[PDB]
Image (tube, coloured by chain):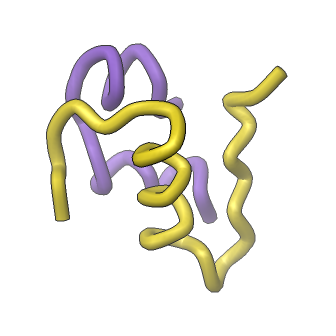
Chain colours: A yellow, B purple
Amino acid sequence: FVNQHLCGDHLVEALYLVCGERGFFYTPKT
Amino acid sequence: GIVEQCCTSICSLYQLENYCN
């Protein structure tokens, strides 16, 4: 997948695509 | 981990792992 400039939403979408079955520590958050 | 390296810079997927996990 799109291994370049992916941000905020596309970036989380990706984090999940990658370890969505693992855990999902997407924070990097507020 | 991801942001100013893979979004606002580039290391994308390879890196993603390292934090998504």
Q: Where in the figure is residue A4, as x and y percent of width and height? A: 16, 39
Q: Where in the figure is residue A12, as x and y percent of width and height? A: 54, 50
Total residue callouts: 0
Q: Residue furthest bottom?
A: A21
Q: Residue furthest front?
A: A9
Along the horizontal axis of the image, is B10 left or right of B6?
left
Q: Where in the figure is residue A21, as x and y percent of width and height? A: 63, 84
Along the horizontal axis of the image, is A26 left or right of A1?
right
Q: Residue at x 27, y 44 (%)?
A: B12
Q: Residue furthest right?
A: A30
Picture quarter with the N terminus of chain A? bottom left
Picture quarter with the C terminus of chain A? top right
Residue A21 in the image: above or below residue B15: below
Front in this rendered view, residue A28 or B21? A28
Q: Residue at x 60, y 75 (%)?
A: A20
Front in this rendered view, residue A9 or B12? A9
Q: Where in the figure is residue A10, as x and y percent of width and height? A: 41, 47
Q: Residue at x 51, y 43 (%)?
A: A9
Residue A4 in the image: above or below residue B3: below
Residue A22 in the image: above or below residue A29: below
Front in this rendered view, residue B21 or A6? A6
Q: Quadrant of residue B8?
A: top left
Q: Residue at x 37, y 46 (%)?
A: B15
